[PDB]
Image (tube, helix red, strand yellow):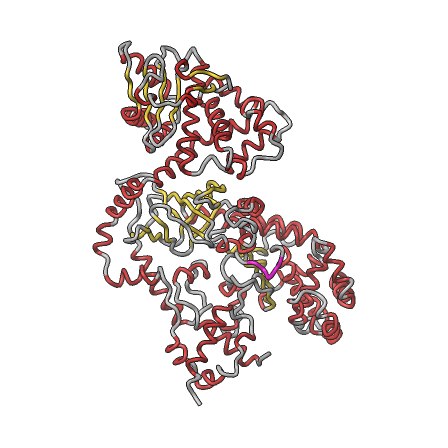
Amino acid sequence: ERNKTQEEHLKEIMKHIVKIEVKGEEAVKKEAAEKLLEKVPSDVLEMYKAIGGKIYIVDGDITKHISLEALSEDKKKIKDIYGKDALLHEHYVYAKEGYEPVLVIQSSEDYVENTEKALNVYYEIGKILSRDILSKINQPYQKFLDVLNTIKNASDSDGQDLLFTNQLKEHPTDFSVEFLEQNSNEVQEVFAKAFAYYIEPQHRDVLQLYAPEAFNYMDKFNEQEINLSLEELKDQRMLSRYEKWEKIKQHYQHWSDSLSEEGRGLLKKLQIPIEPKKDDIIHSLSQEEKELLKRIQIDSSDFLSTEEKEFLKKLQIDIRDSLPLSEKEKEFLKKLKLDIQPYDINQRLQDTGGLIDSPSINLDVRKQYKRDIQNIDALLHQSIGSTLYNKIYLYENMNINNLTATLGADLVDSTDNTKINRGIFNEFKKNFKYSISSNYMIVDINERPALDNERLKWRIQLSPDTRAGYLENGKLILQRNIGLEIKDVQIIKQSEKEYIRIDAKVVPKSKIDTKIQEAQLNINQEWNKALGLPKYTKLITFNVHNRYASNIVESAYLILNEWKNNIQSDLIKKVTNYLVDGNGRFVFTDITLPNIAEQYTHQDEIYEQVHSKGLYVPESRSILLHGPSKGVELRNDSEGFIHEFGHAVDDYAGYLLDKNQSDLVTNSKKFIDIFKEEGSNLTSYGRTNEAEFFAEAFRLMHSTDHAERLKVQKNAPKTFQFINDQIKFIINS
Amino acid sequence: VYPYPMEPT
């Protein structure tokens, strides 16, 4: 009842591109042409249509046709699917290239009994697919280069002995995107050829026999992926782009016409954050605060990013129209930091992962943000589902840093900033299975060019249920708390520049949350048994809310295996138990640290919050690890985590000392001296203070890279010996 | 609270 729509869809498109012009009562020859083109993936025909192509089923010497009247002696001599040279006016198929593509097929009685012709026809169709269609959306590409390479560098040469020419066979190294750059026709042939073998039922088995990797590709591509190709092709068409924009503009017409003034004011301040105003900041500053603002070398501290540094710095300039540093001021600045933040709603949601009630900001602003959010939530009430259309893809241009600053640091090739580093790419695609949107996604109806720092191009498949708001500029504002499943990640070329296309499908946030919850439950069964804790204890927690969601979860495991394989099993158990006894937690999250209870719950003042890659909270006996960022030159998260476990070791040892109080062993005079001496030998960060030095040192000593283990030994021996004492002390005592 | 700060975005 739904397959028939497909046959229905066929006849439709046929009506156009398929034009018969024969002698032998067309009713038959035509019937044959339908049975032949019926084997070809429906969407390839609509794509051919989209680019103005046409299929002509004529009689006799094919070159004896209007469309082929102009063919140049060179393009009059072809080569069949097998490489055998032929003469056009003697063959039965030909696909004319150009800004007015032509497919001419010689009307023959049988194409069934003749598995050879059919193969060739499909080969010229495949040639159309790769050369005339895919080429308009920059493909085949890297994904295909992969199938090609797998074929050659595979021990079984029979793969090559079927799809590659000798030109490809000889080529030494793998085929790089560069190769393809100046060999498009080469790849297109192979593509076309494999498409051919696949399409023609008889030669399909052969493909799957000697070139499985190829079969697979062409299989997946024709059974699904292709439809996305058609989608991208359409996105290139001006009229298609606008026909789409209109239907949607229409589906939300009432919603818009009825939208109030305030309504628009909200949608507006949600797209462009309000920066803090001097006349207010200055005005707010208490008498002493305002005064104290003059003895400050703002550039002194660190918790103030350059933007903030400069901003603050210009506050003096207005006050001057008149007549390191202490911690009382350090306090003053930790206070102003909060006040000089832009009022950025979506930002607020991302940072809190949706917990808009977090006491990580001053009550009044917390409230101001809640009011507006509860409102936008009310405004974005009408769902996208409509009778004006079915599947609807929306696009979003994203910055890799938003998901993982660490990989984002080496995403673009440093020699050619137009290419994407296959290395970081692979690592980035690795465990990216699901994503979550805690703030309002602002997507485009039709895909648009990106910004420089944006090398991520999302193609999202909305659910009819998904609510959204329409913007005049052709952008939709989706409702918060969306669930997204990653369906495909690949490298693509667009505008002589490489991008990572992410193909995602919207699903119920709960479905994703359940996965997170099931995982957190699983990870404890495992590490409770390893560490030997009570079967049902809650040690590790996944506080995952943002877009690189699944990853946070999959890296927690790996982080721990590292933690394990580098530190003494008995040190792990002794300290870990200490933590559990105090309800401690290993928190892996993607929301900024000042929004994790484990830290804010035990805060004195709010301005005393810390956001970083890692953090240890004695009061909660928990270790927090923020995944989306990049630790100050930490190779990876494993290290940062261990560094924190150092602060934990410091916290237990000190306790074992004088059990009557929670003091750090890193505070003992004996250590305050080792630090005063060797405390400048290891990482600069270690130079901060004893606790950080102890941890920095503790970390290097347990690095997966011994080169680093040696550094401590021959640079901070007095320390390397200290830490090792503390290790035995804890292990035994 | 003993951290290990990230790198300014």
Measured from the top left, where is residue A280 in percent x and y? 38, 77
A426 lies above or below A45: below
Task: Name the magenta segment's main secondary structure.
Answer: loop
- In this rendering, does residue A584 appear at all? no
Residue A389 left/right relative to A194:
left
Q: Quadrant of the C terminus of chain A?
A: bottom right
Residue found at x 39% / y 21%: A94
In the picture, the quarter occupied by the N terminus of chain A is: top left
Query: In the image shown, does A609 or A707 lie closer to the viewer?
Result: A707
Image coords of residue A727 (percent x, y) = 74, 62
The residue segment tinted magenta is A630-634
Residue A67: image location, x then y, percent: 32, 23
Picture layout, residue A294 above or below residue A509: below
Q: Is residue A620 magenta?
A: no
In the visual, does A704 lie left or right of A89?
right
Q: Nearer the viewer, residue A234 or A226?
A: A234
